Amino acid sequence: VSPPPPIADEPLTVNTGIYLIESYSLDDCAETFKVNAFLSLSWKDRRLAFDPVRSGVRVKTYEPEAIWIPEIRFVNVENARDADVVDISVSPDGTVQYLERFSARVLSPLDFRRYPFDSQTLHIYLIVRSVDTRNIVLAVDLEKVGKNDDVFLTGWDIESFTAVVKPANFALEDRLESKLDYQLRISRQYFSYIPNIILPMLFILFISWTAFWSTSYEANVTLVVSTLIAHIAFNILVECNLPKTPYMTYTGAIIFMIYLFYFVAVIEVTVQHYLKVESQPARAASITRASRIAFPVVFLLANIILAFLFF
Amino acid sequence: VSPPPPIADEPLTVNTGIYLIESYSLDDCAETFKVNAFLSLSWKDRRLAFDPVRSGVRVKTYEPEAIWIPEIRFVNVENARDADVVDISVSPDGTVQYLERFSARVLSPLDFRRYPFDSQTLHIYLIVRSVDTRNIVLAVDLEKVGKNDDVFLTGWDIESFTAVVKPANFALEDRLESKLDYQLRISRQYFSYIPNIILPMLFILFISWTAFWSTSYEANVTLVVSTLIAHIAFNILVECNLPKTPYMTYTGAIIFMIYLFYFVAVIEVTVQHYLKVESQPARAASITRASRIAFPVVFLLANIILAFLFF
Amino acid sequence: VSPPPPIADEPLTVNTGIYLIESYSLDDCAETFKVNAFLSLSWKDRRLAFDPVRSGVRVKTYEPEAIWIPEIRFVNVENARDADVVDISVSPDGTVQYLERFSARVLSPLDFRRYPFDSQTLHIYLIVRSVDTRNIVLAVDLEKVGKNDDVFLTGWDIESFTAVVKPANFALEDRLESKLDYQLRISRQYFSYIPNIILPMLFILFISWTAFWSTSYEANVTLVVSTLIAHIAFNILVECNLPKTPYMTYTGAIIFMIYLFYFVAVIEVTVQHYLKVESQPARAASITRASRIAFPVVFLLANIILAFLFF
Amino acid sequence: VSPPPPIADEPLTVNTGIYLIESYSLDDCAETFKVNAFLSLSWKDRRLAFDPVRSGVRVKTYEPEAIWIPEIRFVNVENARDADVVDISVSPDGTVQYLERFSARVLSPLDFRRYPFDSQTLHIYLIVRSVDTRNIVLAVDLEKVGKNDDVFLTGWDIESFTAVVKPANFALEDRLESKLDYQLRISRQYFSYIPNIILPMLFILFISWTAFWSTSYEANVTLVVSTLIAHIAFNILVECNLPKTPYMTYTGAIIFMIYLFYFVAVIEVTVQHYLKVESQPARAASITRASRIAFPVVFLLANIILAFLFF
Amino acid sequence: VSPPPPIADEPLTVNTGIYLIESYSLDDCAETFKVNAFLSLSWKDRRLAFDPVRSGVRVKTYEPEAIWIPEIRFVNVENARDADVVDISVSPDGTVQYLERFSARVLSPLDFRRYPFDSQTLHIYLIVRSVDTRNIVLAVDLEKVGKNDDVFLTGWDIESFTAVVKPANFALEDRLESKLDYQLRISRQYFSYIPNIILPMLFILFISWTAFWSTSYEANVTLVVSTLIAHIAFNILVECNLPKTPYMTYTGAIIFMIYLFYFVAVIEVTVQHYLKVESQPARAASITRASRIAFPVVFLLANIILAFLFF
Ligand SMILES: [Cl-]
Ligand SMILES: [Cl-]
Ligand SMILES: [Cl-]
Ligand SMILES: [Cl-]
Ligand SMILES: [Cl-]
Ligand code: NA
């Protein structure tokens, strides 16, 4: 089989549609997600046209091998999609209506800057390479683009599934290629992060601040050092759940800034003890009394500045 | 091969049945489970009918390629099922008896709200897309729906395996789809959670309450801070075994509330020490004496309120 | 091809044999193991019979496609076995001798009650479904059941590989099914658990008991609380290496009981201290002196009781 | 089909090109990366030549099975590449133009010496073995070597994708092998390592140095020992993210040297206490006062020496 | 296709050769390694003899399906090898030259006794089963056995790749089997273990011995207990990187013995404090002074004894 010939000099229009059946496995570290969907293709092949009168059939079914099917591939897949042809239907004018069910692991980058309050646009790129005979161009049949209502992605809210109707036509290895951009808009469900990471992390920090109402250096050293260890435990936990970014993330900034607070609290605790030993507890008392106000204030201000910069 | 033709205008009824041989790999984080079962298909093809008196053979056996078999797929599978045809038998009237053995990874969401005292309903959705010639409709042959007695799912009690007899017929991409709902009812074996997570977590909490019978700030700071670290270790362990939910879970609520108890115990320990230093140990003594009663009481009440809200 | 016809009304006897070449990947959590073995099948097909004189050969070699081969499956496999036909030989009297080399992931439950001093019986179930023409029944050719001497299973002692000669015949979806039980008997190599888990765990517990020869509350609180943390670390390590059981395991019981010892040691340490502060160190001295004997005694007795209940 | 015959005694030149579509999964421990690219092959086969004017068709399109294609393999792949032929085009003169889309896991060693400030040269080796008829030789068509602009590798900057134009021709198992070297130049994005590993690690070390402004042995022991534990936590974290090297890495050297600092700080803390107990706090005071300067100075110098040796 | 016929009663000699292209993934816990190599096979099939005059070509090239190929398998593979036929060459006399490129996961046991100073002999066993017609026997063509210079195995030194020329011929399931032993000799690169596990582990141990120059029970309890925790952390790390052995390993012995040192140090620290409280610090002083010498001496001697027993 060869491509359908041009009546006039026109390129072949392959109408496409993707209908999500299932979406799963959004791997943050890998920046990948798995998809299970219907891929619909439609093109005109005059060679397959027939008269319904002499045939007695309004449609004609063909096996994939029997006819010419445009070679449609996904740009951003890990391995080539697992596809199973559902149905191939030919109308009397030779209009082919193809339908396959596929599953693929899509590689699409994520912006972690606002984690865990981030939204993402996942992309699925359809592509077709033009042949020497004729040029092949993709189009979106919006009637055949959608998603099942039950489509869920664990830990994410599925906003929309749409297609950028205008293809990106360009040359690659001395042949033209028509590229289409399907978009899955999702926003992270930040709920869990509050009682699991954020609040426990604030409690341990506030506990370190009780050292500002204590004169016992040994108790203070314990308070500040122990809580610092718990902060390291959470930092490590967070960095395990995320890839290494060339930028700072929101949570990453909060976490880093909290280290400075422990470092300064250690300095205060050290200073207060030194003065007490040098028989000048009145200076020490002033610093400790200031610290009780300064620490929550500077912490609250820095957090406002950060949230402002990030949102 | 093409679909069997309608005598009158009737849709084709494909009788289905799933018989579980094995169930395994219930992944809580992935919200998936693996299944190994028999899939039975039954439909009438008059073109295949014969005479039992003259043919001498009651049943005719065919190879998949030889006859028309309806394209039955699973909605909620990760990848398309691994299937092996066991047998195809044709009765004289042309009733076809298809039997395949398959294995598949089923994606079915889980409700973690009552963890680890939760029960789940796992779903397996069968589907058939109607052809242009005739409409195909699924039905449940309850005779051919079941499970082996030895079917086990590690850490779960298998309650039942049933099918919702009435299919969900609906239009999808200008064709009829017939969807069936097979249900696997399971309930979690919470036993282990008691000596592994619950009791150790209560012991460490109680140990922090011994600070209410001590005047040593340094010892108290150690008691409360150390036990708090062990609580963080268990919180992290629990969150590793669970996916990120947009809601609170039972264990999650208990764990979160316990943090507040440590935070308040630190406050009390701080307050008691401050008063002792300000040479007013009678006030301190009152607060500590109150704490000895208040802490177990408020803990026990809060737990009743929580269990009430969750069950 | 169709099944060999019955001379009299007899069922077809398929003689089976499994010869282990390799045993590996015993996953405790998954309750699975991988196997690489020879599967031998033998049955009589009169239609295949010949005369050695006329033919000039005493054996006939066919390709799988050429003859009727019984559809033998494994009940307890994750996915259908990876098989490669080694040879198919026909005797003049129509006795077929089939040999395949296969590899499969077998799902077989494990009894963790006596861990790490447990022995297991791994099962491999062979099955055959009867056809409408004739009934098929499995048998064990003990001459063709065995294992290579070099077969090893990391962290386990391979006791025996035997077959239960009498098949379990039963009805499934109105057809006779012949089930065979091949058994691999193994016992765990508990050696490692002594210097890795058991002894370190006893040392930390004994270290906590040095608090019984100390009057320093602050030092005691440190001794008891620190060692308790190390015990949590080991409990978590152990539970990672094991699945969630609806029963208690031997190690699990020891681990749980040790928690009670830390809890009581904390009480003693608290009591003693409280006394000293109330200016009554003679009572405190009595309790501490009792504890020095009581703790090792109650620990040693409880361990005898436990070992008795478990073995 | 057999290879195209030599006009004169010349070896067959297969022009090659690799165009990266996607690059992902750079596993540091495994020293592997996954690639998705176009593989282009061009050679000339006079048997396939035709007339442009007479035939009317400028280019003829064949199916892989129809013509002779050189057996091109990758040297450094884990498993043989997953390839799908996109197009085969024959010019009148008989120049074949082959194009496949492939995906493969490439095993290419990494130099960890400068981690996390390292750059790597990933290799992809193309190979062809000669046949008995004629010798096959590879060449690079630089016009068909490249990468998509959107090619990204998480945690790395993609510098270049080039080919060493001249093949490595050599004999292996008494036949000619023609090997080509495609190079992917990448440099690590060290940004993250600063707020995640480097800075937290320096803070805990500076905290240990506050022991130089304290006379409390008990507080010092806590300061130095606790911070040492946090340093062990980071060392373990780092070694989990890296393979075992027969050499020292930059981070590895910093980490190791920091251990010496804790060891010496413990000695100082021990020495200072011993003198204080021996009623000679003037000597102790001198050592502690020296330590306050010596520690940051020796640390800063050693780091300069190390960075010098490593860069 | 059937086996070639004997010309006297001789068994068929299949000459074999394995040429390593790549070796990777040496999994210590799984006791497996992955290999990518050429498998060369040579036997003579007189039925394939040809006159170059008539055929035109001096050497004929066949497709695997076209001719008889001896069924060669690997004994110790997890799953059957992934093979791709590179070439099948037939000389006029009928000598067949078969070349395939394969990849396989080889299961070969490891001796951990001297870890991390151990050397291993990895095995790859080739096997052939004799047919009823004629006996097949394997031979090594040493000219076709080797490895690429660039063959590397992360964390190991590749010593040699050789074959035991004499096959192991033996009966199995009433047929003859010809087994060949290919050996890959490797030795572990212990470098990393020194700054990563060994030295940090010694530093923490020595840090505890500073308790021998202190009279502060509270400080000593902290020193000894804290360092003990760090030792548990390293023990766990080490046991994660190793399988459970029925014997002791070198590192395992060192690690276990170090536990005894902490246990005895706790006893000394307890004893010293008890005497100090009983107002007899002169006895305490003697024990502590002895400990300062005894501990490093007994540690150094025990290590000599251990290294002696292990090497
Ligand atoms: Cl694709
Ligand atoms: Cl399916
Ligand atoms: Cl099977
Ligand atoms: Cl390849
Ligand atoms: Cl093999
Ligand atoms: Na302390």
Image (cartoon, coloured by chain):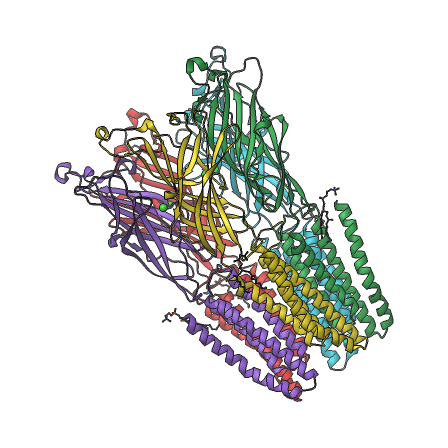
Chain colours: A red, B cyan, C green, D purple, E yellow
**One can see residue D258 in this view:** yes
- Does D163 appear above or below C158? below
Q: Nearer the viewer, residue C138 or B21?
A: C138
The image position of residue E203, as x and y in percent, is: 59, 69
User: Residue sitting at 75 percent across and 79 percent down?
Assistant: B276
> In terms of image quadrants, where is residue B238?
bottom right
- Does D242 appear above or below A19? below
Q: Nearer the viewer, residue E149 or A78?
A: E149
User: Residue sitting at 31 percent across and 45 percent down?
Assistant: D72
Position of the N terminus of chain B, as image quadrant, is: top left
The image position of residue E3, as x and y in percent, is: 39, 27
The image position of residue D122, as x and y in percent, is: 37, 57
Q: Is residue B152 left or right of residue D256?
A: right
User: Residue sitting at 45 percent across and 75 percent down?
Assistant: D305
Q: Is residue E291 left or right of residue A108?
A: right
**One can see residue B268 in this view:** no
Task: Residue at the far top: name it.
Answer: B54
